[PDB]
Amino acid sequence: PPTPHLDAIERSLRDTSPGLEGSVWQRTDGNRLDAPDGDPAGWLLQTPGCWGDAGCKDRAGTRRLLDKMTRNIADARHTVDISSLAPFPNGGFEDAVVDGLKASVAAGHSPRVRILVGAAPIYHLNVVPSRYRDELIGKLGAAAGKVTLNVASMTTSKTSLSWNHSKLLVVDGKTAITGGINTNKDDYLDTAHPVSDVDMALSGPAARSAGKYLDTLWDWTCRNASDPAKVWLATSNGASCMPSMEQDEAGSAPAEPTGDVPVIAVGGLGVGIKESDPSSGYHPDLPTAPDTKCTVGLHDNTNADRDYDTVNPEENALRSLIASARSHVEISQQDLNATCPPLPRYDIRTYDTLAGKLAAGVKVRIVVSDPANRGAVGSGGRSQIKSLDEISDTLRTRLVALTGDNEKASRALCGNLQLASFRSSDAAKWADGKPYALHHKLVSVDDSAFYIGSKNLYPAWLQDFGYIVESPAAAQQLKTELLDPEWKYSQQAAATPAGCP
Ligand SMILES: CCCC(=O)OC[C@H](COP(=O)(O)O)OC(=O)CCC
């Protein structure tokens, strides 16, 4: 079974980060999209899960995701590995962890558990590692004595604004849930205006790849607990820091296959974990582009740092995913552009790839969060543009820079671009009155290969992770369950750019 899209991505990653293969990125065969029997598309865990229901009575997607998290942890024989943006998991998310651990201990196991969050410098952490550990111990009750906890909050770079943004739940190195959902009450659990998000569940060797990736983050975290400005660490039962928990669990034999799905795991190390991939020959033609009305003051790691690429293969992974599309690409995001300053407004190479596809007649669709979404720096569902023209107009100038003339750029822009903000029903806003917020980090290409993960397409220099799947059957489930319903309702919020019929 051919995988032309995974092949193009694999070439990009091996030229970018050959040294990081097997830790920060890895291609595997034999994975299974982990759907419960009777629900073939249940591996796709969308939230809140109320397509075409403006009042969203039944938050059935959020209940399936928590149910799935609880069940995967309950099955744990050996290791539980959790990462997210701060805060530590609370609400139903903590209940899922606590309930799962009690069940695993009750089945006679003594699981080791890593819970890592990334914290921004300006962010104040109400519940710190030691307090969170203590809450866990208390709710676990008698079971705590059999549970080895490592809990840690971390920040890799104050100046380059870098900390963990990956959203992972890996159990025994063989099941993995990942995506864009924060294990964080307020965003998804207790509001009549809940953010729209998506996760996926798999099993197989690509779960071990996620495990390896978290070992990389914990090697750094354990070592840099020597600097409490960077790492806060708490363990239970006198346990040591466990930097290589996933490698110890893997052992010598290679991961066993669970199905037939080929997957590329790929993350990135942000800034301040590893300066560069010492074995990488990557030497790119970095784009000479200016920006209309923003210049980043910080050093532009997205658009002008070779070394950053070599330790962040996810950014080239996403670009070569779009580059790989022969027919059509769907981009469903919270944002394509970033707030500038502090970060660059956009990823030049990404917009050049998109423009190149518009000029080749490849259909491009961009659905982002509504610009009416104002939030704080990390609100989730917030928008970082004031208008959708800040995407189309950028696509235009990058088209003119390529095609030569503006007329040719209009036949490309108006002919091949669909640009909208997110809706999940016929209502323009929630029946709550507040607007729809989108939190996807999703790219789909030719209904064959897709990315689901935590890594946004807008510039951020955080540590992220995600999976690229190539499977015509799985992209078809993705199209039916998410992409078609998304466009069915977000086209009522479509943009028609400047200079177009
Ligand atoms: C600031 C540059 C990194 C960034 O942009 O951070 C976005 C992230 C949320 O990202 P997202 O989930 O909305 O895509 O917020 C945070 O990590 C900071 C919260 C205090």
Image (spheres, grey):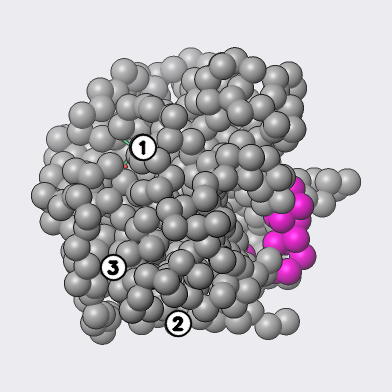
For the residue carrying disc 1, how many other residues have a C-alpha within 10 Å: few (<14), some (14-19), or many (20+)? few
- In the displayed structure image, the side of residue 437 where residue 29 appears, left or right: right
Q: Over which residues does the magenta segment extend?
A: 462-481
Report the residue marked by disc 1: 386
Which residue: 71% across, 45% down?
A: 488
Which image quadrant for residue 125?
A: top left
Report the residue marked by disc 3: 309
- CA–CA distance between discs 1 and 2? 37 Å
Q: Which mark is residue 11?
A: 2
Q: Give the mark nearer the N terminus: 3 vs 2.
A: 2
Residue 472 within the magenta-colored segment of the rendering: yes
Which residue: 42% across, 71% down?
A: 407
Say if mark 3 contacts mark 2, CB within 8 Å.
no
Q: Is residue 464 above or below residue 281?
A: above
The location of residue 95, given as percent across then percent down, is 58, 23
The location of residue 479, given as percent across then percent down, is 71, 56
Q: Quadrant of the N terminus?
A: bottom right
For the residue carrying disc 3, how many other residues have a C-alpha within 10 Å: few (<14), some (14-19), or many (20+)? many
Count of numbered circles on the image: 3
Which residue: 63% across, 45% down?
A: 491
- Amino acid type at circle 1 is Lys
Q: Give the mark nearer the N terminus: 1 vs 2.
A: 2
Helix, strand or loop for disc 2: helix
The location of residue 362, given as percent across then percent down, is 57, 72
Question: Is the CB of mark 2 within 8 Å of ligand 1?
Answer: no
